[PDB]
Length: 121
Length: 127
Length: 12
Image 1 (cartoon, rainbow over the protein chains, first blue to last red):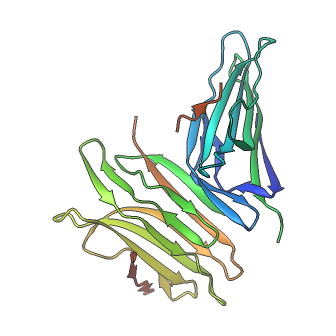
Image 2 (cartoon, chains in turn purple, brown, yellow):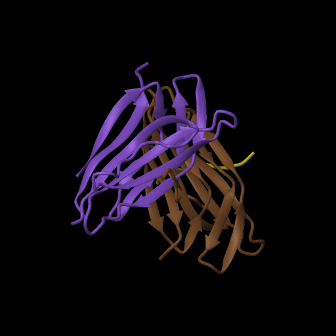
């Protein structure tokens, strides 16, 4: 299954992230760096599609353009054949990776949905 | 907290609706009647202000004047004291209730954001 | 500035 990890951090996301029948749905929300700064985050969704032979790793990245302040989503899809793996390859500032799921050929999903909330006041 | 409910409907709104630390923000968007007609919807926002004594119910209405086709926002606020409730009452056709939240004196929010979708999000590929 | 305020009904 995909376990839900509620976790406190300086950088936190108010977007609702959930597992659906077909994949992952992330609602529109806000990225916060503590009390100081807030950035708008668009909604995003993707299918957790299995492969016939290999398990498939899905890793969702939340990164920021340093110049424009635009916070965007990136998705890595890797086939776990001994050479495939997920690692953020982009040139923007990686903030977090709230979804990490391995989908097995028979449809079994194993991984984590990270839900970051504010450190306590 | 404030839950999000996605639903496939004939009437759907492309406006982004989100909870902020102070209240609710609805972006400018489009109301769609399937694939037959689209109507412009203005941005709207409001504070989820608590009361010192009673819990407060917030209700957001999206309604349309069927003759002018003007689509507008209405907000009802109710103080949970047992003497009043929120209910949309006007002449205009009520299209949807996308926000319904109860705000308790200490700031605790309980409710739902209804996000209507098309019947029958690609993140860039970091690959 | 929207929204237009709708007053709550009295119960009863």
